[PDB]
Amino acid sequence: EIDLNDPTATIVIHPGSNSIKIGFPKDDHPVVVPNCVAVPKKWLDLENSEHVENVCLQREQSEEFNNIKSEMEKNFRERMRYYKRKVPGNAHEQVVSFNENSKPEIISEKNDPSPIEWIFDDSKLYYGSDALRCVDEKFVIRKPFRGGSFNVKSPYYKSLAELISDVTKLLEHALNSETLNVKPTKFNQYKVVLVIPDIFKKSHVETFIRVLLTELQFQAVAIIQESLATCYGAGISTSTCVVNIGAAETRIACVDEGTVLEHSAITLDYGGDDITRLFALFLLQSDFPLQDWKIDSKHGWLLAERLKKNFTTFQDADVAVQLYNFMNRSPNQPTEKYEFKLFDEVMLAPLALFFPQIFKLIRTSSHKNSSLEFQLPESRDLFTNELNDWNSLSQFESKEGNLYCDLNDDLKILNRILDAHNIIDQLQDKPENYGNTLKENFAPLEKAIVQSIANASITADVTRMNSFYSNILIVGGSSKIPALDFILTDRINIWRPSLLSSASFPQFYKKLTKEIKDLEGHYVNAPDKTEDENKQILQAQIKEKIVEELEEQHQNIEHQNGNEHIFPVSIIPPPRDMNPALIIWKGASVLAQIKLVEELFITNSDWDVHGSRILQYKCIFTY
Image 1 (cartoon, rainbow, N blue to C red):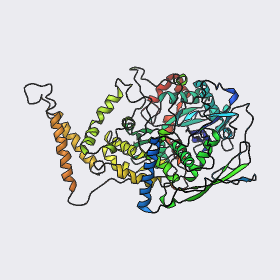
Image 2 (cartoon, rainbow, N blue to C red):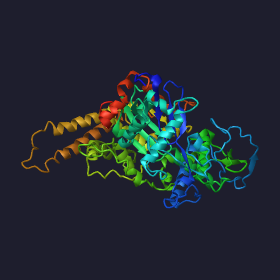
Image 3 (cartoon, rainbow, N blue to C red):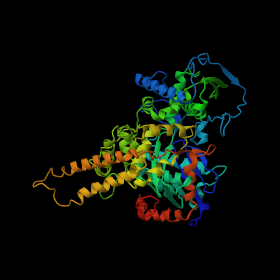
Image 4 (cartoon, rainbow, N blue to C red):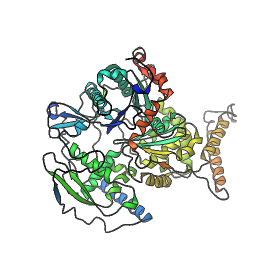
């Protein structure tokens, strides 16, 4: 009952697209619970909204898809030349695919599982790992979460109420488990630390708090943004850039001295899930023995996920015409082992992180519920009525394809950089249906990270550039690809412009801003000419010129009569045998254990008197 700030009585929760991470803070590890609910097909209206799409895929693809895969094949060739080896290649044996029946002795393939003890009773809903064994001829799977937020675009939900009921029943199922055995009538003894994305949607956050306190009846809730949690989960002192690779999205953001820098945040619309889809396709195109792959069905998706997780690498050392195998488990058959050869598909697929346009080519365009979305309006300031979610300069640039890495001269780069504070100003109160609504962000990973880091510095404290480039942490369930650190490092280094590689940029940039400020400032009287409406351009052309002057002065100062100072690119995953999917939960559980959270727990009484308005006063980030 009673409300003390003691960690024993705290549950730390980190929703994600693949699985919700949950446990007590002092746990070595949290329970990992699949983000899945299995619904008997006979319970749902499935005619008009239709797309029984759980049943179809496509080995052949467009030219553009062919072109891009050809170019990926080049990039691969070059990497392999640049270190090691090639061969005769594609010429094959999977054409003549041999399957081998297994006695029911499915010794483990990998991880925590072995054979599948299926669920045939379609007279109830199932949750988590239970949902994962429901036979898909009887059940459909919905997923309450899209990585932190509520999965509004799912078409299996007719309303928030529906969505929330399986959020709460999914949370309950998790909370009731061999290792945490907390039933719903005891929820009011617990407080919750909730992990929330960096660019959270206020209506989701607020709804979730409302749900945890008002319906699940938790004592109190405290929230934290993914990137800060990931810093707590590793080491927070420094300035650092977090790259989080998830199933559906990749999130990048910088963190400096306790805060997640708004204009550094980028949400990229691709992640481990497109790698998985790419991999399946590539396997199909290299004549994979299972040719009709029902990829959006549970059974086939699971198969696609297993293989890619088992097999995809950036490790050039290990890329060889190889024999791989797998067992295809049997909805109503004997278990069939298959053996297949792979060569380059294991790297081409994740290489797509840098040619993400191909991801776009192979998935259907979003089909969000406006019946559901209409019930989660985007947050608006109660006074001005203006969209008031965090809204990041870097998201807007990268989405629109204005990436610094794609600019050639230094002047354009410098000017755009110089323009930033206007671009953010325009952003925060435009005739703003501008900053594309439906548009997905398909910017290549490496260019995105550079964007994030450049803006992360110039919008706040530029002198942290160095520190950012030497603490890029890679984290997230889909980031567990060997040698991702390695190739990412190559690529930032090829792509980062030279202007933005010089370790003295911040110092230069800092000088230029001051000297521009001495043109608006120490000329506070109306410019020299008699008449002035354009006479601000004779100081806007003197600005144009001083830029060129200092820009050039820097370059002559660049020769430096010898050796050149240059930002590193330290990309740092967690050690082999740590799980990158769990840093965040770890970090949250560290918050959960310290003096700080005490001040940050929104309690029920907090919430009934004040509503979402407490977030303005109890929150580790400026809400």
